Amino acid sequence: CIPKWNRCGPKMDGVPCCEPYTCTSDYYGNCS
């Protein structure tokens, strides 16, 4: 998963932010 406060892209890499966190943009954004 991706560490909080970092770039996340589950639709482009297949790995969203960690369960306790969420991604804002599926293409390119941040987690919090």
Image: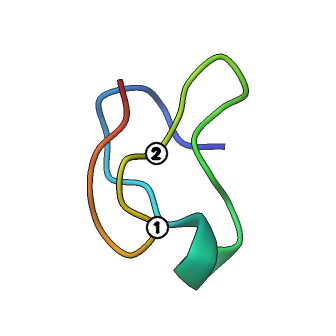
Binning the other alpha carbons within 10 Å of mark 1 as few (below 14), some (14 to 19) or many (20 upward) gives some
Determine contact: label 2, label 1, CB under 8 Å. yes
What numbered label is drawn on residue 26? Answer: 1
Q: Is residue 3 left or right of residue 6?
A: right
SS for dot 1: loop
The image shows residue 31 at horizontal and vertical percentages of 37, 35
The image shows residue 28, relative to residue 29, as above or below, that is below
Quadrant containing the C terminus is top left
The image shows residue 13, relative to residue 24, as above or below, that is below
Residue at position x 65%, y 16% in the image: 20
Q: What kind of residue is marked 1?
A: Asp
Binning the other alpha carbons within 10 Å of mark 2 as few (below 14), some (14 to 19) or many (20 upward) gives many
The image shows residue 15 at horizontal and vertical percentages of 68, 60
Q: Which residue is mark 2?
A: 23
Occupied quadrant, residue 28: bottom left
Q: Nearer the viewer, residue 14 or 25?
A: 25
Q: What kind of residue is marked 2?
A: Cys
What numbered label is drawn on residue 15? Answer: none
Residue at position x 65%, y 32% in the image: 18
Q: Is residue 16 left or right of residue 22?
A: right
The image shows residue 8 at horizontal and vertical percentages of 43, 55
SS for dot 2: loop
Q: Specify the color scheme.
A: rainbow
Residue at position x 26%, y 56% in the image: 29
